[PDB]
Length: 275
Length: 100
Length: 9
Image (cartoon, rainbow over all chains, first blue to last red; front, side):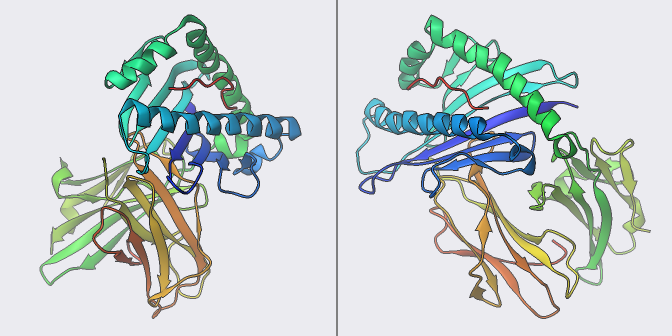
């Protein structure tokens, strides 16, 4: 199916306590593969998936060089943004940046993105055409004017359409057993009495990959969206994901209820019933 | 500034079976800013060997982290996750329930 | 692979 590569960067200032903390992480789809943490001992980009450990020293040296340069640009940025917004030197602030690319089923370029936030709010974001920027205020319009200039525009375009796509495909190939897999959810249902007149039915999806899934309850074929407790999809920690959906059912009505599961690993969506 | 409260889930990696080794997870998500304290507890006491994932964030910029540790559930041992964040007036404790 | 050519805000 479709795939993406994304890098996520977080920089947090801590005034009086020296240098801003900087964290970088890289994902292919829902699988983390690299990290850097400025507070760690190594000062290196480090592998976080077995399939990227195969990359040689030139890869690790070059990624380490670049991620430290990223780190430095963010350190500068925190100061610039404090200047832009007339903020005091004493408060802690956060910048976040995400960039990357999507490919479709044919592994051809679909979309490129580059987005930036200050203190949890949209600051500037690259539009889908890859030339124009959405600036969220006046300060961001100042940045927009810097990032709009001829040479800088082409360079980001050459990364997002070219390099990001090439490297995504290389990773997909090199990490095939992990990245090109589809793990169908293992599903079951539990029933617990909450009183003598009501019970909870909970529909479980476990051990699935990728994270995208739909779990829904119906009563007599009617969606119970407003009465379903649906938890956020959550990592099991072994590279797979979990989700559940629960309904409270009056006693005797269990057979009216159906749980419906859609996932790319399932050739047909599943319908499950307590019976 | 923006402050969003952590959502908290406590759960095991595998269906809990008494006497079988497993991992206990506390997944914290949807929070901002990123400073957070998260502890796993066994019968009220802080588990010393806890690891966590590398800080990442969602499309809306809000952060998420997975905290985890090896455990072997039994019938009587109680597990919980204890989270503190700027949006919380005191540490929030969520007990581990094996069917959640 | 990271992008190698970042610009300041």
